[PDB]
Image (spheres, rainbow, N blue to C red):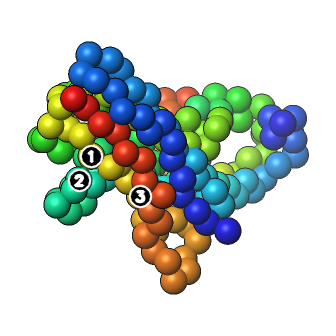
């Protein structure tokens, strides 16, 4: 449901025990996202979709 | 509250397959290291199987490596253990163990009641 918040600028997901962050493939819609924070999680591979 | 309990205890002659189980209360199983220990008459608690949190990697002792199978089922909030034609000398009382869950109070090691499985 975060994919619909087109006006987001900061996303903080501290200590959410995120394992896979492949949902980055859907964050290109947000034209104002500048401060994606994913610290304090358990993520292995940064997805190729950062581009 | 935090408590550990397992089931599946039953005496089975050599030649069958027994499916153990467990039950964890008060914490998720994914964010915790679950352990299986064996207890035998006249013998102390010997480690058997361990499953690592945040990555789900299985760790086995050379005593029973390559025969057991451990899996974590977060749907039931439990840990399932399966044997593959365990030897008669493998009879023991199996203990579950989870240590240092996200909650940090005086009991740091939680053990199950204990189930006795017999092989003959």
Residue at the image position 54 percent from the left and 53 percent from the top: B5
Q: Quadrant of the C terminus of chain A?
A: top right
- Residue density around tag 3, few if under 14, some if 14–19, many if 20 or more, within 10 Å: some
Q: Which mark is residue B97?
A: 3
Q: Chain of mark 3?
A: B
Instruction: Left or right? Give the position of B77 relative to B16.
Output: right
| Quadrant of residue B58 within the rendered picture | top left
Q: CA distance from mark 1 to mark 3?
A: 16 Å
Left or right for B94, reference B104:
left
Tell me the chain of label 1. Answer: B
| Closer to us: B106 or B56 | B106
Residue at mark 2 to residue at mark 3: CA–CA distance: 16 Å
Q: Secondary structure at mark 2?
A: strand
For the image, the number of numbered tags is 3
Q: Which residue is mark 2?
A: B40
Name which of mark 1 and mark 3 comes first in the sequence: 1
Quadrant of the drawing holding the N terminus of chain A: top right
Q: Are marks 2 and 3 on the same chain?
A: yes
Tag 2 near tag 1, CB within 8 Å: yes
Q: Quadrant of residue A14?
A: bottom right
Instruction: Report the residue at 55% width, 35% height from top.
Output: B73
Which residue bears the numbered disc 1? B92
Residue at the top extreme?
Answer: B15
Q: Nearer the viewer, residue B71 or B64?
A: B64
Q: Can residue B33 be seen by looking at this rendering? A: no
């Amino acid at each position: 449901s975060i994919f619909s918040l087109h006006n987001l600028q900061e996303i903080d997901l501290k200590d959410n025990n995120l394992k896979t962050i492949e949902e980055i493939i859907s964050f290109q819609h947000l034209h104002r996202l500048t401060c994606l924070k994913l610290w304090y999680n358990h993520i292995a591979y940064i997805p190729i979709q950062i581009g | 509250q935090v408590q550990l309990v397992e089931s599946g205890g039953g005496l089975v002659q050599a030649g069958g397959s027994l499916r153990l189980s467990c039950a964890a209360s008060g914490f998720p199983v994914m964010n915790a290291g679950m352990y299986w220990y064996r207890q035998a008459p006249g013998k102390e608690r010997e480690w058997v199987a361990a499953i690592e949190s945040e990555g789900t990697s299985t760790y086995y002792a050379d005593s029973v490596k390559g025969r057991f199978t451990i899996s974590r089922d977060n749907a039931k909030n439990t840990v399932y253990l399966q044997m593959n034609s365990l030897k008669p000398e493998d009879t023991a009382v199996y203990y579950c163990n989870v240590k240092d869950v996200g909650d940090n109070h005086f009991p740091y090691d939680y053990w199950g009641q204990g189930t006795q499985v017999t092989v003959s």
